[PDB]
Each structure stands twice: as structure tokens, then as C-alpha cells.
Image: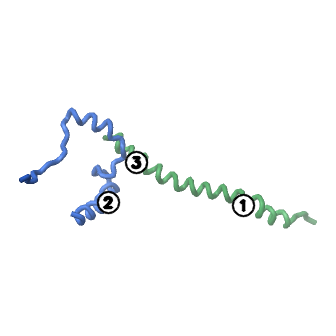
Chain colours: A green, B blue
Amino acid sequence: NNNSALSNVNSDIYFKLKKLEKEYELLTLQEDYIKDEQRHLKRELKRAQE
Amino acid sequence: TFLHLPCTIEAEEAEEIGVEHLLRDVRDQAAGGLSIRLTNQLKSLKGLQSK
């Protein structure tokens, strides 16, 4: 019975998964970005109110 | 002799309008929120210390 390969998963890890891993590094970068951007609208929020 | 007599910048009211226009910077010292005055308090210690 059955039909599966284990060869395929391992291959997918070296090849395809590494390119997804570059993309997850970018979402890290996004994380950092929206700290500075949050602080900035906070400065502007005060300036508007004045 | 030349004796020091107190001075400060205070601005005229008519001047003010333009001062507001040309300052579009966030102002590191402006006396703002919690954040602005924790930056100040440190700045203030090094001010005095050098004096």
C-alpha cells in the first residue's frame, strides 16, 4: 500500500525553504520599521494638537 | 569695564508667527512628553557639569 517519498521533503528544505527564509528576514525588518513609524506619528500627533 | 548683565531670548509676538513657520523640526528640547524630558534630564546634567 501507500506512496510517499521522503526524498522530496529534504530537497525542499535546501532548495525552496531557504528562499522563504530570506522573506522571513524581511518581516523582521518590517517589525523594526513600524517602531520608528509609530514614534513618528506620536510626534506629529502632538504637533497637530498644538 | 564690561560687566555681564542678564539676557534671554523671548521673541516679539509679531516675530513669533514666523518662528513657528520655520521651526518644522521635532525638537529634541521643547519640554514635551515623558520621553522628551528624560532626554533633557541627562542633557541638563552634562550642561551643569561642564559649567
Mark nearer the viewer, 1 or 3: 1
> Who's the residue at 33% across and 52% down the image?
B28
| Label 2 chain ID | B
- Most distant residue in the right direction: A1
Q: Which residue is mark 2?
A: B38
- On the image, the x and y values in percent for residue A22 come to 67, 57
Tell me the kind of residue under disc 1.
Answer: Lys
Of the two numbered discs 1 and 3 on the same chain, state the one appearing first in sequence: 1
- C-alpha gap between disc 1 and disc 3: 37 Å
Residues packed near mark 2 inside 10 Å, few (<14), some (14 to 19) or many (20 plus): few
Looking at the image, which is closer to me, B39 or B6? B6
Q: Horizontally, is B2 left or right of B28 in the view?
A: left
SS for dot 2: helix
In terms of secondary structure, where does tag 1 sit?
helix
* B26 up-or-down from A2: above or below: above
* Residue of label 1: A18
Which quadrant is home to the C terminus of chain A? Answer: top left
Subunit that carries the residue with mark 3 = A
Tell which of A14 and B2 is nearer to you: B2
Image quarter of the N terminus of chain A = bottom right
Location of residue B41 by image quarter: bottom left
Compared across the picture, whether A44 is left or right of B37 comes to right
Amino acid type, mark 2: Leu
For residue B2, side relative to residue A17 (left or right): left
Label placed on residue A42:
3
Disc 3 element: helix
Residue A47 in picture, x, y percent from top left: 35, 42
Distance between mark 1 and mark 2 Cα atoms: 43 Å
User: What residue type is disc 3 on?
Assistant: Lys
